Image 1 (cartoon, rainbow, N blue to C red):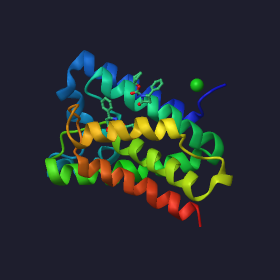
Image 2: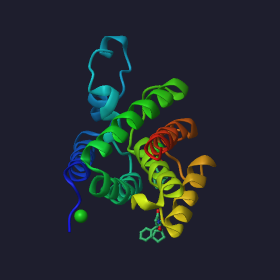
Image 3: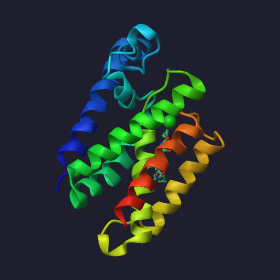
Length: 180
Ligand SMILES: *C(=O)C[C@@H](NC(=O)OC1CCCC1)c1ccccc1
Ligand SMILES: O=C1C[C@@H](c2ccccc2)N1C(=O)OC1CCCC1
Ligand SMILES: [Cl-]
Ligand SMILES: [Cl-]
């Protein structure tokens, strides 16, 4: 029993980066991995994605990776690595875009991506049971509680509601496309 290669490599990468952040401090790692925060950086193309790899607390990374492991892992197993890769790239790009637009380039984390995955697995199951992909009732509840936590700032997070929504929109859009 094991998480697929994308699911696994993403978790490893997040952990390595989290470690780098402990050794060097958050700021220094952000200096290299954050969304372009200066026009002289706009052509360092890894930055449009690598912001998703940074986490700022234990909770952040523990919870993001837990949801990534479960939702990302299920999508990878049942729908393929390619599917997970595309959901990840698109949600990371759009949620990052929306985030920097409203609040500037200093942010990070897999939240945009897990919102997408959450939206994807849920809607897919709603519209296409026979797909084998669905979000259990109990998990819908826990997902909702964390959405509330982020919406009303019960727990301080890196990204704002807008970027979380942008992540969700991506997942819903792809599930919708997929269930035609
Ligand atoms: C990202 O939004 C950070 C939070 N993760 C999250 O809320 O994900 C839920 C689970 C399914 C999608 C919404 C977060 C949670 C706990 C601690 C810190 C950050
Ligand atoms: O988020 C989530 C899903 C739920 C959960 C359920 C079982 C194991 C781990 C996580 N959860 C969460 O926030 O649960 C809290 C209550 C008990 C563990 C932490
Ligand atoms: Cl595993
Ligand atoms: Cl966040």
